Image (cartoon, coloured by chain):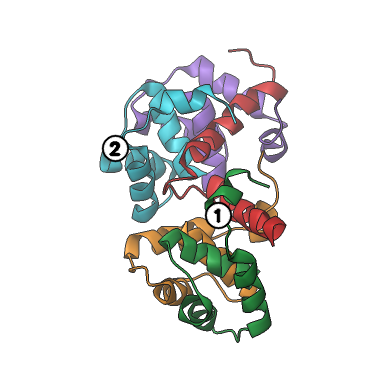
Chain colours: A cyan, B green, C orange, D purple, E red
Amino acid sequence: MKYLAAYLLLNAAGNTPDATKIKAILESVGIEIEDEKVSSVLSALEGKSVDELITEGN
Amino acid sequence: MKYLAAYLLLNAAGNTPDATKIKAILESVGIEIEDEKVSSVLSALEGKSVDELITEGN
Amino acid sequence: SALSYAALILADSEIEISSEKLLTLTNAANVPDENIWADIFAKALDGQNLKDLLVNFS
Amino acid sequence: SALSYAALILADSEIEISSEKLLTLTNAANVPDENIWADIFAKALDGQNLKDLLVNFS
Amino acid sequence: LVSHFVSAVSTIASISLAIGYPTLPSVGHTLINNYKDLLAVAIAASYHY
């Protein structure tokens, strides 16, 4: 999906947030972002170690 | 199915019974409930740990 | 999730997964309506084969 | 990889995976453009079913 | 009904994993999809990084 790839791509570069980057990447794609989908992904992201979740593969 | 999703949805909220909720959700769907199907699901539900059955996934 | 369970019941009943229809099942459950979460949910579900997603999964 | 994540978001958004489209998402991320890496990426992605590759994998 | 429950539970679970809609159960899997798909593009191709 759009959201998933966008935050993952940023994570590789090493940094992310609502307006500054998530909104910027999807907008660079040329797509209009749904705020609710960004908010949900960010709220889920808080207090999570993205690198650890990757280390098991599923 | 209708019944399965309805009790599951309630379980997430954390509470359920014949008239009070099962009947209420399906009626909120706009569908007429068969009593026999509700009765069967409830009778099956008694003395079961729904959370434990979920923990194996099948 | 109450929102995911609400979607699967709405499709099983044969009714479209929109803000009104999710809101009526959600209200029957007794869980408070939150605009952002059902809005993301309808948006995530947009452009989907519910049937094809439902079956594979590890 | 930022380049792999950029490709999956571009396909999810519905936009073609070419040098301009990867460059705009890459710039929005803030990562510097490198001609060799995105050219390479388009070339690997040429002649591909993105959908068929995405699902199997050990 | 146990089989149907577990299958219903999987429908929800499936919907959750694939859809990306992060209350408590789904979340770690949803993140993994965005990789599963990248790691993946590598296996067919023939650029080495």
Residue shown at 68% from the left, 47% from the top? B58
Q: Is residue C21 above or below residue D39?
A: below
Residue B49 in view: yes
Q: Are marks 2 and 1 on the same chain?
A: no
Counting from the top left corner in percent of width and height, residue B11 is at 48, 61
Residue D26 in view: no
What chain is tagged by disc 1? B
| C19 vs B26, nearest the viewer | B26
Disc 1 designates what residue? Answer: B49
Residue shown at 70% from the left, 27% from the top? D57
Counting from the top left corner in percent of width and height, residue C35 is at 33, 65
Q: Nearer the viewer, mark 2 or mark 1?
A: 1
Disc 2 designates what residue? Answer: A17
Label 2 amino acid?
A: Pro
| D50 vs E32, nearest the viewer | E32
- Disc 2 crowd rating (10 Å Cα; few below 14, some 14-19, many 20+) is some
What chain is tagged by disc 2? A
Label 1 amino acid?
A: Ser
Q: Considering the numbered disc 1 on the image, is that residue within a helix, a strand or a loop?
A: loop
Q: In the picture provided, is A33 more to the left or to the right than D38? A: left
Distance CA(mark 2)–CA(mark 1): 40 Å
